Image: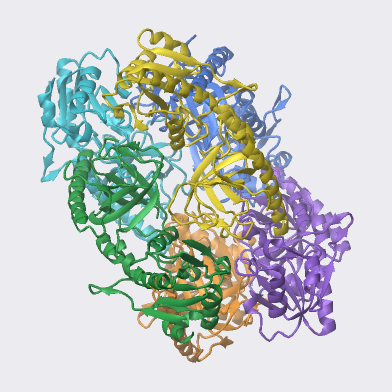
Chain colours: A yellow, B blue, C purple, D cyan, E green, F orange
Amino acid sequence: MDIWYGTAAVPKDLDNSAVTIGVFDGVHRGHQKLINATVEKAREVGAKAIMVTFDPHPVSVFLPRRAPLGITTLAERFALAESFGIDGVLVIDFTRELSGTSPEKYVEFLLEDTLHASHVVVGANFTFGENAAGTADSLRQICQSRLTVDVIDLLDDEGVRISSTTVREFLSEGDVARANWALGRHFYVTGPVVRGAGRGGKELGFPTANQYFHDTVALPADGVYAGWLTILPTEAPVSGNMEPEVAYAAAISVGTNPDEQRSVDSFVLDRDADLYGHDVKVEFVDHVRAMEKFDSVEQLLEVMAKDVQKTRTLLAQDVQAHKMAPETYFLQAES
Amino acid sequence: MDIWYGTAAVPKDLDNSAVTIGVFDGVHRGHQKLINATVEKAREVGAKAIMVTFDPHPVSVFLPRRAPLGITTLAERFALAESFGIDGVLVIDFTRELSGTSPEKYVEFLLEDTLHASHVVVGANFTFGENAAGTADSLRQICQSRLTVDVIDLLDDEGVRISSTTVREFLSEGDVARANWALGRHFYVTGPVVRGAGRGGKELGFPTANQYFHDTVALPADGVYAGWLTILPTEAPVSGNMEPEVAYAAAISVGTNPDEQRSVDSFVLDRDADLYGHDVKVEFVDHVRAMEKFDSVEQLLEVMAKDVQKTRTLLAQDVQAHKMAPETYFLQAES
Amino acid sequence: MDIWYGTAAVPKDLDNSAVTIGVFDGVHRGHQKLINATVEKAREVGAKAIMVTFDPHPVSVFLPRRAPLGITTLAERFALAESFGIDGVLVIDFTRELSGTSPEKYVEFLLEDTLHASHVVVGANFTFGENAAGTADSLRQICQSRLTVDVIDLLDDEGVRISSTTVREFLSEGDVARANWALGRHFYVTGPVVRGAGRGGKELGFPTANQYFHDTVALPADGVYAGWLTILPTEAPVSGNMEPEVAYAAAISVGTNPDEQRSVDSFVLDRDADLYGHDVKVEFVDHVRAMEKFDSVEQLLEVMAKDVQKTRTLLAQDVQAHKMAPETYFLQAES
Amino acid sequence: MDIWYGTAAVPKDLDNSAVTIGVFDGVHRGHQKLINATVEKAREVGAKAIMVTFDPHPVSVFLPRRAPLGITTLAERFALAESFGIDGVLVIDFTRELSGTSPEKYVEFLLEDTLHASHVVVGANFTFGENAAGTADSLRQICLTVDVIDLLDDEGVRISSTTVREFLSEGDVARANWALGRHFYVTGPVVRGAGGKELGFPTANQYFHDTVALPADGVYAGWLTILPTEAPVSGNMEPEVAYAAAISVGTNPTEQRSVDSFVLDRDADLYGHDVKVEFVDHVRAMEKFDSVEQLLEVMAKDVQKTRTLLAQDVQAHKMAPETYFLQAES
Amino acid sequence: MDIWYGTAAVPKDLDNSAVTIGVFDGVHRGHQKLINATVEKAREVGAKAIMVTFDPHPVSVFLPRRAPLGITTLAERFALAESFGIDGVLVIDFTRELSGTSPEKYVEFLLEDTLHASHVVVGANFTFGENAAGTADSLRQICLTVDVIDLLDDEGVRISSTTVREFLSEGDVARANWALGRHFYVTGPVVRGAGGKELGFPTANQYFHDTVALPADGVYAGWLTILPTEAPVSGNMEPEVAYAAAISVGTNPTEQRSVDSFVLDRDADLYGHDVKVEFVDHVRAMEKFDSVEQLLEVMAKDVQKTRTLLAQDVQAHKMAPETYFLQAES
Amino acid sequence: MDIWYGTAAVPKDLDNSAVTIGVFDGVHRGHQKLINATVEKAREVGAKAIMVTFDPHPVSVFLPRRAPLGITTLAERFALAESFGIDGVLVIDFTRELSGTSPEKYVEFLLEDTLHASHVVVGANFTFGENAAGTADSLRQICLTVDVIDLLDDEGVRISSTTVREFLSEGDVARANWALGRHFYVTGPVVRGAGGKELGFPTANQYFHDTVALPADGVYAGWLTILPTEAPVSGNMEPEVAYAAAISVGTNPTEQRSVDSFVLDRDADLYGHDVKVEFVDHVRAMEKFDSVEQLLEVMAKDVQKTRTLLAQDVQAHKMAPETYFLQAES
């Protein structure tokens, strides 16, 4: 999949495209409707399916450091776009271009001159141009004859509007199950594993993996979650009895540095391993409990054992729910 | 108007004075009663009207960094004193002098030896001398024969006690209208304009002016306010269509750095300007709304347009209320 | 009293001991039951009475920077142990040894090989060995024949469980009287006195002593307390009219730096002194009031005088309660 | 003078203009040659004299926080351009536009479509377009009359923003001033320091951010002016008069810079006012003091030396202020 | 290869082993002599080749934050040991064990009870036990065949972790590489910088913590490789190919280090990928730039010099990468 | 000894006194001449010997955070004054009083009204009143008998707070001690470091703020004393005995100072105790270590050198401690 930063990086000999445009933060189920429609039309006419997206977040251009939390990193947005069949992503920076352009010139410059589009797919909530004057309705009238426009309704399901906003609200409440339901997959983060408390292995109380994430990353509320930890493909040696590319059952503690840097510390069920130096994916399945303070090692280990018990039950159920479950996983029936 | 720092800076040949003594933070309507009485008596007897005030705040001498927030800067206290007819301000630093003096020696040294006063005006709540032993009643008895004393009742109006404390409470609640009512003018701050989000001009979403204030400055609660922005007299060129010395209608967003440094970002109605490098006065008129987070540029601009609508209405009313309104102003009837 | 850090520092020719094992944070009334039983048995058999304790806190090994607040410093734990008749303290660091040992090998290595114990005294809640598998019951069965075991019930009195946890809860609520009741003494801190607001002496509003404590130190909730300040033995000269080794009546303000560094500022009743450079012990007796903000020096001094009035009453009562009262004290009947 | 941020801010009805282009940092004597040529032409033809300049500094776009120190602020660059008769400044941000463009489309977009220029004045070192391909040579060929002006050499010294920054960093403010064609200055609010009659408390305390070019740490002779204000002044100073001053430039150790001004023969405290400090000559390097007696002695010597140096500056009145206060002795 | 943290992590059923012991920082050519001897023996006897190493660095236990800079990370130490055929690494933390022990009980506890060693390979400088009393001499007497290998001297230079750190600190990466027996490298994620087609925006921006040994600030010729990934790549680079690159090493002033790579003749942005940067030779010391023209000119000269140096590296292909991209000219 | 903060704290019924005035930082041998003369007179006449001193340092009032480093703390200044027989110290804060006053009213307010002095002893360098106008000369004329004592010169060296600070900054503690008339020392609480029997873990770890004068970074021979306490001591040290020690002075890089004491032939941990560290002579400059073997070797050499130097100090017993512990060998 091609990735272009700014209109000037798009190949001049681009022949034809079907285009979808949006922030696409999270690539949730509504976003997938736009992408699927774009891919389908591109196939039909023998064109490239192109996503136009935005980095930095358009809100951050007006209100620096008050933009919405990123449901996914830009990199994972690319990975998700590719997985749903996008052939190219054009990333637009509103501090560089297209911020002060009229709706008419926006379409002329972006859709026609740059992308040579024959079809554009946008959500009902789409806006564009100076002071957000262009709407989904405007785009339909501006693109009369010149190219076909498919405006897709926002997705309402089980009485909830699926949007980046609603996914962020679920995460903030610790309702990862509802977040997952709206995303169409397990919410996840990926990152390197650092040195933490003790060394991973025989001690139940030392995490298998310690990670830190910056305060622009959307994470579930502080607490303990059932989930799956996967060591991403690697030839580096692994300390202990975990293999790369397998989803291992884990109890995951999300915390906040006492400093809004967040910690994600994973306790892998029934395994003795230390994952320092590896890149790992952590997917969240369900909430287990709120954070609490411990007054003794005995009490700490007791609560950890209960976390393991409930995690095992939640994950045994997740494996059945199954469109989301991992293809290759490890979960023991008991300790 | 003369400004003296410490008793030693007062001219030795000072002939005669009528004196008022207090912190005078805010120079609110009660303070104005003390000042007006002092100016009147000074005129009658051909004397100088002198304010004795205190910097740092007397509370900060005992409890550093727990003094009350400054309603105005010391500099603006001077400007306000001058505007009500004070001829000289004596600024006393309790870390340097007069902290451990008996009431008797306080009067002897300050009022007689230093200021050569024939009249003193104080509020009913006045205290002085070591461990605050001197009261308004004490001053009357100590100054028998030697000089006349006028003790003025604290101001109660519309069932509220007008004091620096009550003004601070109104500001903290976001009730700038009540603060203004107690002050007898629009609450304001002045400062240099810095570089902020984007550049001021055609974009409705970029502030016309970005400012920052230290955490010792009393400001209204975080939120959006209707008010007036004035570029103070200057020969420096101005980017865009604002002229110096005119009060321009503005929607003002008061925020807090996510760090208790406060931001004041002003969106000037119907103008396209960037005020970087200029000193500006921002006066607050009324509360418009609480702060909120924005999930899209469309939503942000929508709320900003509603802020403008309500600001225009509040300011059209302010112009009529009129003892406070600015003498030279710009406010369009519509966008 | 001997203090050994780690098993390797214990004398190889140690002949015989009666041992008690625990964190012992606070050396509260329950802890004293364990210590008293250990001292008694050691005397009976002509052995050394040994405390095995832990630093860092065992919880901090698993959850760094989330361990419980220290009721006392390690140093004061030593001082308290000595005062109840302990002959030696062995300090174990679980990052260095005994963390991953089986219960059987824990007893073999620590109690037999290192301490040559003939008797061990533990609380009903005692655990030991890898993943806390050893209990008070396990210890009894493991030590069959080899050495006698006395397991002492946790102390319940007046419907409260006396534990380090309950003492910490009382302190956090500002209930120093209940904390004191559980400890069997006045809760106290000791530290050097630094330069603070003004200089101690004639001014009622300047503290006699300013102190700061790190955020790992358990202190009562922010507010004002009645208590006793003692200058610890010293030949250094003392500014003002306080003598070393006398408990002086004081109103103590506990605060928090606006930074979780805590301040303890003591206003010594009826004394004029500045304690810069001295080490001082501050013991808490009862809560007087919550913290408040002051808008004037008059108001500040008024509240301070009321603090003195209530402090004098609370301390006059404390002197009668008397098992805790200080042996040598200064408290005037009136100002 | 108008100020436009970006090409889209420029009025569409701009009928005609004479344009000069450059960073113009310091608006030194070489820059004045370009501006003077641009203004003379415009006033001759009744057209607007336009300066195209750059913020952030073009280097900082490639190397953030490794750009050269600002000889003046952008605000003072506007003030100086206006003082030399420029009618409009267009400020270009290379992170927003005119970066990836070729020389051909740079000239078409900027000079023709945006500014409708009939005349353009540039330095011999001028470059433009992607990879700095465009040169003063490349501009001439593309038609719009083009005046290319040699870089200024005087007394064997190349006058450039670089050579001015060198003089300042070395503490040689006299040479800096000679290259600038005026006294180097900074302007800013006065903050609280230590308050007067006492010789050792500064009349004014100021701090500056680390991107501001200042002379090397040391003591300098200069002039302090209170900028026009109706606000009251504590002590015996009046606004809009240049007062003789010994100026101590320092660094906050363990690079926020301090500029503390001791005004000669005046007893005043300038807290809250905006003040202009112009530097005339170097007096001495920084030193540490072990007693008050020593400090006050060296300060009296700073004053003596300052009087002499400023007396000379007044006589060679080309750069001296028009209304000033300076006593011959205490 | 297995990795065991502490003696208690080692399998109890470890029947037999050939062991080498040391800090092994950098796994330089002297270290390879020890590892090669340990591996040859084990493969001969069908036993496990074991490396006992130390984290934290033994010096840091006595002098926290005064330990020598890490030539490689502990992770790269594992990767290198595995590359030379080591079957297990035992990592010892001296704050947990083997510190207060005598030489006798060190050997008994570590080599006999834990590793069941029949052969041990150590450097002539090896010491152990409390107060570094144990020596290579003291090890021989205690029976387990012991091979003590002289420290490596080549071309009149002692090859040690110390001499490698010296070469790096001086900017002499060529000599560092000669002592290492490979190109010195670092690996890490690429972060955001300034985004391409523009020569002056780096292809990849990286930062490193202050315990990482890096060459002296300056510009170096090297190779950048995108580590194996299925993630998409922006621009015309493929994973697992070594691309020619001019690498600028810098320091965040007022010691976080930056490593910014300008990949020759490629237009790409490697944000979010993990990248290996190997250093071949020094090009130039750091310098400041006063214009874009100057910056781009020096960058073109960096590219020219880099092409030449890398051409030489390719020819002397002992340390050169197996699959690489390098153009003879623009 | 009484301690009064400000003139208003002094008892009104103070009937008579002999006064000395000065900063008295370090209470060096020149200061002792003034104090001795003041005490002898008072004890002769049965009056109080009074020292008027200054906090903050008078320089810091003019130049905050540019004052000279404190040779001792104010607390140790009180302790030293008391040790030389001073009956009261009056501490003057120049930001509170005696600043704007003339020489005449300074003497009237301080010496007559406040202290009721019949005798005053000052150094030849003494100044007072606004702008340091008052001198030792100006004091004599104003009647109160006045003894002005020359500054101390010995072995061709001027003994002053300045020359003591110079010796310390250079690492020449022997010369500092000679000028002081005692071993230079600091006192403070011992904090946690790395815990013993191990030679390389310090017996005591301390930190000091950046206003404390300390010798240059390096290793020194000295004595460590645990100050009187009933608190238990871990290991084989007793309170109130001076133990031989190798003392490492260091700086927290990227200026908090460390003082880490390795007590000879003792196995102890002094966490939580207050400790006095006195410096006798310089052993070596700081160096970096690349191995534990090297570190322990140099530490053994530090111990050997320390034994020799302290043996000499004991013999020339004028500055040596009265009760000490020092072994001739391990």
Seen in the picture, residue E235 relative to A239 is either above or below; the reply is above
Could you tell whether D233 is left or right of E220 in the image? right
Q: Viewer-proximal residue, D24 or E210? A: E210
> Is residue B42 at all visible to an observer of this figure?
no
Q: Quadrant of the N terminus of chain C?
A: bottom right
Seen in the picture, residue F215 relative to E80 is either above or below; the reply is below
Residue B153 spot, x, y in % from top left: 71, 30
Seen in the picture, residue B217 relative to A231 is either above or below; the reply is above
In which image quadrant can residue A184 be found? top right
Could you tell whether E10 is left or right of F255 in the image? right
Q: Quadrant of the C terminus of chain C?
A: bottom right
Q: Viewer-proximal residue, C308 or E96? A: E96
Residue C334 spot, x, y in % from top left: 82, 57
Residue B76 spot, x, y in % from top left: 51, 33
Q: Viewer-proximal residue, D102 or C233? A: D102
> Is residue A332 at all visible to an observer of this figure?
yes
Residue D271 spot, x, y in % from top left: 45, 40
Residue at image x 22%, y 44%?
E299
Residue at image x 28%, y 49%?
E323
In which image quadrant can residue D159 be found? top left
